[PDB]
Amino acid sequence: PIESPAPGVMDRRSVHEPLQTGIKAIDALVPIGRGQRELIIGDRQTGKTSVAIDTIINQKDQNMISIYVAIGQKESTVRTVVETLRKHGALDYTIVVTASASQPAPLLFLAPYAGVAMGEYFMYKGKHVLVVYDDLSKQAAAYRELSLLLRRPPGREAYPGDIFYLHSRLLERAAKLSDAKGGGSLTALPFVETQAGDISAYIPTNVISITDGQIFLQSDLFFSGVRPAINAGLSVSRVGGAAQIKAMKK
Amino acid sequence: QVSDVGTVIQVGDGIARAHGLDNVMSGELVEFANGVMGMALNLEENNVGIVILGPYTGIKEGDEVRRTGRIMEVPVGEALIGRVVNPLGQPVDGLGPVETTETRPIESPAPGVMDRRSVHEPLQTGIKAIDALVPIGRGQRELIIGDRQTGKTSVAIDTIINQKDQNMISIYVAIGQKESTVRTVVETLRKHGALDYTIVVTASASQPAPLLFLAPYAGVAMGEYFMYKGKHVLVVYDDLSKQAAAYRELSLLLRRPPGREAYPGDIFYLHSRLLERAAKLSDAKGGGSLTALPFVETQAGDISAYIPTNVISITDGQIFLQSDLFFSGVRPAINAGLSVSRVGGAAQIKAMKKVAGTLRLDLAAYRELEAFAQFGSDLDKATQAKLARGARTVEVLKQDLHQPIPVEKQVLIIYALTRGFLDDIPVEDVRRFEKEFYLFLDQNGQHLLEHIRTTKDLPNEDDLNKAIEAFKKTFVVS
Amino acid sequence: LDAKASEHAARMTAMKNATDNANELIRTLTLSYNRARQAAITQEITEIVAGANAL
Amino acid sequence: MTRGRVIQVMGPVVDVKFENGHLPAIYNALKIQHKARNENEVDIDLTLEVALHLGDDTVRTIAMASTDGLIRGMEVIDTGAPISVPVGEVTLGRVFNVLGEPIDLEGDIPADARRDPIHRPAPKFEELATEVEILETGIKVVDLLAPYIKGGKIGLFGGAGVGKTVLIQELIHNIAQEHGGISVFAGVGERTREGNDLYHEMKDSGVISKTAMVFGQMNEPPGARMRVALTGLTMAEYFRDEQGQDVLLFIDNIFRFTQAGSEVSALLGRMPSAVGYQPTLATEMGQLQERITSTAKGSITSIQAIYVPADDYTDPAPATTFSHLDATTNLERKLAEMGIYPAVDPLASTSRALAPEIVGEEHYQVARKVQQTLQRYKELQDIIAILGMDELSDEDKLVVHRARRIQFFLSQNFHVAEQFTGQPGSYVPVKETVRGFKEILEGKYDHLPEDAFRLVGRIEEVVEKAKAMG
Amino acid sequence: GLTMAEYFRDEQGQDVLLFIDNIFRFTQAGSEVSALLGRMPSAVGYQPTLATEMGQLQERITSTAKGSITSIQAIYVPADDYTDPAPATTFSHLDATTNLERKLAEMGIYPAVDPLASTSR
Amino acid sequence: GLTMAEYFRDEQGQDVLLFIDNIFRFTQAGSEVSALLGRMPSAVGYQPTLATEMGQLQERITSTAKGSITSIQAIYVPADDYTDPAPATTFSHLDATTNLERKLAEMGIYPAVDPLASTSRALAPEIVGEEHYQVARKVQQTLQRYKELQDIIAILGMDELSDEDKLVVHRARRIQFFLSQNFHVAEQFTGQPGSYVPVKETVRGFKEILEGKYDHLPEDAFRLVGRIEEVVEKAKAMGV
Ligand SMILES: Nc1ncnc2c1ncn2[C@@H]1O[C@H](COP(=O)(O)OP(=O)(O)OP(=O)(O)O)[C@@H](O)[C@H]1O
Ligand SMILES: Nc1ncnc2c1ncn2[C@@H]1O[C@H](COP(=O)(O)OP(=O)(O)OP(=O)(O)O)[C@@H](O)[C@H]1O
Ligand SMILES: Nc1ncnc2c1ncn2[C@@H]1O[C@H](COP(=O)(O)OP(=O)(O)OP(=O)(O)O)[C@@H](O)[C@H]1O
Ligand SMILES: [Mg+2]
Ligand SMILES: [Mg+2]
Ligand SMILES: [Mg+2]
């Protein structure tokens, strides 16, 4: 089913297994563990998709299934991403779910739930899954369009009242199951596109209030040669560090 | 039968709802029981929504509404010349009825893309600053924008007066003005003789909002009758901001959703419809043209406001007037820095074109150096020459009230200023020098005057030099 | 005399660059004010629309 | 049956009632034709677009013209398909009005002409091209520092009187000459006099024989202004889908499309979104932009001018539009007054294509080196006024000496600029311009006078000019 | 009050002075009436009919052949905001305006009229 | 949870620690469900009954004669807007508040409590002591003066400030850094073990800083330490 209850309090285990993204500026100072959900946030043309593609490609050695969910992306961009995945061989273990900007609003609203429901199937078998949501801001815009068409009164910035519940319900299904539930895990990397780096906007704050950290990419750094564009001032991992190899931690 | 009659079921705030009128057309005029006109705006399934165009206190529930069979139009013809009239064509000055035999609808499509021609004819406003810095061509529409009490109405009246010998018809549309103000404007026009070719359309602040919303469209409809016959028309809308306010009131009374800055959604469409009907017709349609001078009032000089931005996006330029310049004794108050005409300059005559550039440069230069005013003498080149010439330019560009001057005299005085014949004249005497120069020209330089007036070109430079030197020989500095 | 003229030059350039800094800060603050006010405008429009709709 | 009657008229919105089981589909076209039976009526000729199904066999529509004169009870006819405009060779050199009806006096279009629906789903994921390709425009600045992409969207910016129109004409000329394609210009909610001026300029330049124009300007209703872009796009799509060509599509102002959509939504009665825009803003923009893509047999690339309200690049309409753009070219009044044409800013312009994966290592290195040189010159221009020209170091003198020649060599002579300058134009291939800029970087031409680079095509013409000068 | 004043110039041909305590409170009362009647609020919550109400009040204060009425009106500016709709739509009907400053009042200069912000035709 | 705590308060007369993880989500859920119940929307989309619904919950969490309840609540602030109705209404229900700030969090000084927005009902001379009250007020005054100087510092530069303003800035930056602390639970992010600082130690250390004793130490010595002696230890490690 699209809508399913999240794992309970006693069904979960503390994250203790590293997710090696293959990028120094992440694996060194903002580590990501399995079962974590880490936010990738930045402006347009900053490398958000490139970070996810590199992370997905790096998982060839590891025993992990990858799901790339594109919401509101351009179809040419999705085609080129699929071609890079095919060239690097990541299509041996990858599922691509797409809903372009030409699709009606309900499909944009619905895509991430389909992705996470596809992930849960492997998660509950004791396997490890990685899920990438290419935009949650565009999902929020689609849901706002749906609510206004249904004549529900808007709240702050015309968003409906349960814009928080939407994202929390989506992202709360990513978990690290315990040995009693099988030991499987699901990892989420939601994306948020800010406007002029305003980290204090409504949707960025809502998504920050859910995930276990955030990786902030700065356009000022991306331009002028700092190409990975990591901003160590605003990037942190709340659960990471306990899921980092001893050598790197040392 | 209920096909040609209807009974009112709701009355409120100038909006009426009537049952019946099965054959009424959208946009039609209807007749109430007591003689008040109305528009059938919304044709719903079981009732008709009517916008009242007069005092609605005399309309109750149950009184009959009669159909007329005519989509809303206004009377047109040469008989409207020299009369002040309401937006519906009913005279308000007395003097009996206006006898006309032709009409033209208020809504009418703008001239097509293939019906137009490039603007090539000058429109002499009679103001030195406008005719030199921001020329206006026939068929252009140019925005005039400023704050309260800056001189926009005075500029419009001066432009209308200056058109006496030209082959143009002027139309003055006053929206939201005080009745005494409109009366005074009409009296000045009559005193200066402009009523021989001028129509005044008035909609005072005490009128219902739909009349204010309709007035500029009635003015344009009156102008188009002359325009399509091959004549040239000048139309002035005194307050598009007040027209927009009246439209916002009407839209809110009809309970339409608001838009940006609380103005309605199609506020841009309103002024686009209004200002797109002014054009220069091609030769195949007859060489007619209609030129428009919309007005917009700002708040503390803020241009970034919604309505100013919309109108600047619509029109072909802007004339910006400054409150500080107006208060500092510069009465035309035109800021040549921000002001710009995009289609004009092509229509400017050759004599003015050959001389306007140096004055443009001088006036542009004498604005940044005014910051360095606390100290007097940095350089002779930077301070002495530049500041002296700029101050003399500011003095010559000043103008008195209701006294336009001809283009050839403007050209001659601007040439004298630019070439340096004012270099050794004190600043305080420049206006007297200009006045006595015009009198001396009338006395002796009829040959130069007629040469300019016939060829639209500068006369022989050496002869002009010797004439100005001959005048300076007699002019006394005191 | 040389030192007095040096004092004049130093104070002149100090006032100049102070004015430049002040105008930069004014640009930033006024533009910030202007980005802020559109949120209030859209909030009041949203409130009016909701009030009209709920009835 | 296929016949209905009008039951409500409220401005541009018209409600029509049909027989049960015979309602038209969404986005279909309905025709109203009427003859005044007596003096209390007027003749009517109108087209309606279906928008909703209100229930009770009633359909709500949007009119493409003024609704004055409508009477409750007039007969309505169903066409059984959306708006259809003529496509093919007959559309070249003609001007249309969003309904496909010609505006110029060359006559009507015969009824046997093929017509295509306005509304159409975007091309499938299967049909798209798998690789990114560069559209060779033949203009040195664009081909070096801001490459174009087949199927990409380009945003154009610039002040008044800088060269946007002449640049558009030169782009059409170069594409038609070398790549064998055509162009379609779609004005949207702009000045009618500007449209007439553009028509006359195209006729003067001779570009008009290779282009089609649809205008639907400011004075048109929102229903027409909201579909001008779609009709222009659907006449453009024919040549790419049926003849496999590379096509240009110019949209005069994409912001007016969004504004017309918002106006239409307010009439439909939907709840206003964040800043008064329609709730369907993103969906409408996606449905317009996603049809401009490169396919297996052809491509459409679009040059779009975008107005930004209050210069706020975070406003919802510019924010939504910018997500689709692939490149950006900015014009400079400073360069225009300096005499550099086509006056493209070599530092404000940005492009997604300029990457080693797409354009090549050699091209990328040359371009980045040029940008660094120009940035260093920009920095040194302050120190020149701070201290003086002679006080700068020798390496800074060399940097300035290279930068002047680079900035001058960025200029080019346009084919359509002959009417002004008196000099024929030049089409410079990307390989040739890369080689020339590498040669200028390496110091091979430091001895030449800097003015011989002023306005010229290939690098060999520069040494020819220097030879003729001295 | 206007009805009481109009008689002296209509039937008796006098010159009358009409002093109005505060236009701002008149506009506030109009806005309250509009909100009670349930109309859609204008720019900052005012009534849509603000301009027409102000016009129908002020336009009756005019000079005619029989007599003249001159009016001295006091306006209240909230938080020094002259952009406020009530003063903004009041400005269009005035021949002379006077600006009073708490800055001048604190120094002790009564009547505290600003000599540069006051204009008259 | 409140019902469970009330039994221990009443039927047993026992002291209760009550922790509420995020009380704002209660009003958020109320606003989510309010629209479907047929109520007209209030300002910024909240329910008309925001104040009464929150009051009916808050006034149950009190200490009575038979038992005492001390409650610590975290109150999320949506989009960093402290004027939002939900944060604004809950202010009147509290005795002591501490306002965390993103600005202080970004500079790296945790716990990032705003030293001027935070207030408590217990900061009175007869409750905490004369010396404590005077030291706290002096610290707040210095921080406010440093806050006011931030425009003149940015524009005219640090050089042109007077003799006293420079001393105020010098003391204020060190005070702002010394307000930071290393936490026991933060040892997961850093190897520093953390500390527990008594009130006497805090008051004496801040008094010593105010008297100008430690003006010769660098600013960075004061970040993330416990008692005042650790500042001297860190400076000596730095080499002083
Ligand atoms: N590590 C890198 N090295 C070089 N180029 C890079 C790197 N990461 C990203 N880029 C470049 O950055 C550009 C945009 O990157 P990307 O598409 O990942 O951005 P984005 O934030 O997903 O953009 P959008 O808003 O279009 O979705 C591309 O030209 C890509 O080649
Ligand atoms: N060139 C001038 N010389 C002298 N007085 C002038 C000149 N231009 C305008 N004035 C005077 O300045 C005042 C401005 O009035 P005007 O009607 O021209 O302004 P306005 O911008 O239309 O203002 P309002 O908003 O009050 O209608 C009037 O008293 C007018 O007589
Ligand atoms: N390549 C060129 N060669 C010669 N002259 C040029 C060139 N490009 C521009 N110009 C000059 O600049 C003028 C501006 O032309 P154009 O109409 O393209 O400008 P624009 O920036 O699009 O203006 P507008 O906003 O009025 O449409 C031309 O009329 C011509 O005089
Ligand atoms: Mg991306
Ligand atoms: Mg006036
Ligand atoms: Mg152009």
Image: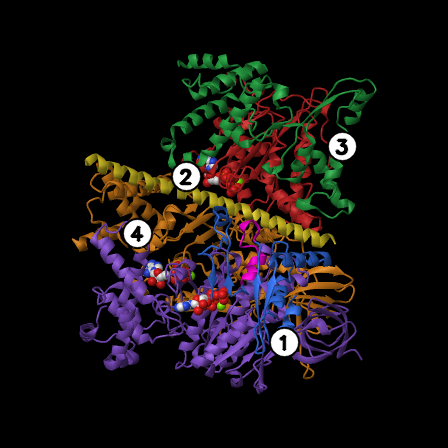
User: Element at badge 4?
Assistant: helix
> Depth check: A41 or E61 in front?
E61
Q: Which residues are magenta?
A: E77-91
User: Element at badge 3?
Assistant: helix
Q: Residue at x 42, y 46 (%)?
A: D350
**Residue type for callout 2:** Pro
Q: What's the chain of the residue with tag 2?
A: D
Chain D appears in which tint? orange
Residue D275 appears in the picture as rendered: yes
> Depth check: C36 or A28 in front?
C36
Residue A168 spot, x, y in % from top left: 67, 35
Chain B appears in which tint? purple
Res E10 label: 1
Q: Which residue is mark 2?
A: D356
Which tag is nearer the camera, tag 2 or tag 1? 1
Q: Disc 4 vs disc 3: Cβ atoms closer than 8 Å? A: no
Would you say the beta carbon of the disc 3 residue lies within 8 angstroms of ligand 1? Answer: no
Chain C appears in which tint? yellow
Q: Vertical placement of A76 versus A246: above or below?
A: below
Q: Which residue is mark 4?
A: B373
